[PDB]
Amino acid sequence: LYKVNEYVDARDTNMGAWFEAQVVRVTRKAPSRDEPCSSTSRPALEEDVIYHVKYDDYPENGVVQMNSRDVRARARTIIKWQDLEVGQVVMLNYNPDNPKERGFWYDAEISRKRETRTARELYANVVLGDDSLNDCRIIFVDEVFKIERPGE
Amino acid sequence: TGKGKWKRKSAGGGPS
Image 1: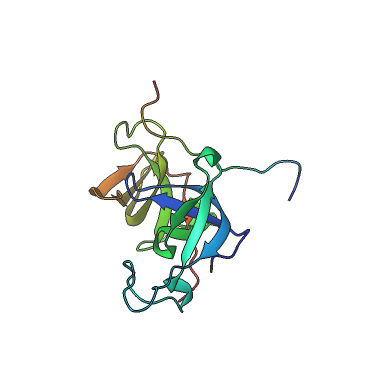
Image 2: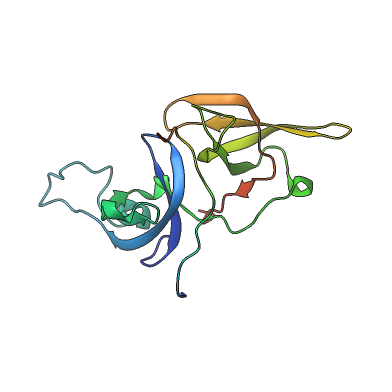
């Protein structure tokens, strides 16, 4: 999963944006006796631990603590128009303030694919850290990324 | 890894 010195991406729940991030340390908090400060479950499973990741773009932050749910391995496979499938989750750049400009790596699923005599249009659903934008059109189709998972 | 690290292209927001 996420080991020290591993290359994984971290997402900011407040903005729902994904950016390159590196793993610096992995740790977990346990209860003093029988009154845990506030954890979903006692430490024991790899998912029951806390991971420390830093943002390469903004390393000044220092050390950030994030759960595995918000941390995912960096994509390693690029999907081309010919390799685009429906129902697959991919990462693309979406800018809610100015969709016609550059956006941050926002997760989204392929909704529908459309081709024209000399133009291509792709439809995908975009989800923000809290707001939803399903049924949205993707201006950039060449920028498509696949998400990798541990498989369990 | 190497002399420097490579980053992926990504930009958004409304810079001033």
